[PDB]
Length: 181
Image (cartoon, rainbow, N blue to C red):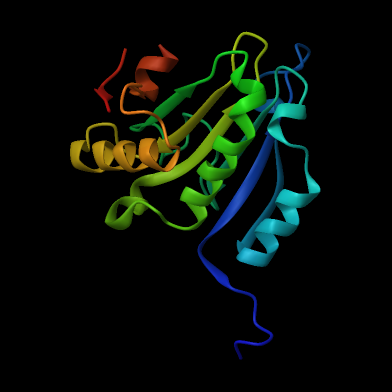
């Protein structure tokens, strides 16, 4: 059995791609790439697609649990928010790809203990003004879950204890930090 069975992930995940096109609405620019629910199928997808650092400005990748669309309006995001990593322009070269892969692994390896159920997904925005990576969680009022996810995340990325990252609610974004670690 251990010799021929793929390793199932705790969740099935969906990878989404966004390309900025001014002809279309934001939602129409968002497309589902594919889904996977094993370790082997994750790496097959990851090894097939461009590194975030090679995407043209204006594109996003989003990895979300199957059934959760990567948008504020989803029932599992509308009360939620995001831990935000803001990258300067030089970090496109040094940190963007390594941080994004670490983020993908935090998701699929369920690295937030009994709070991994609060995780909805993650998003990388490739932007000329400065890239962004974020982990999206389901309820911005859940102080224990949000602060635990942020503390674990900051350490898995290896950010110096000097650096401060913020958590913002999607309701505020759509219309400040709620937490910092």
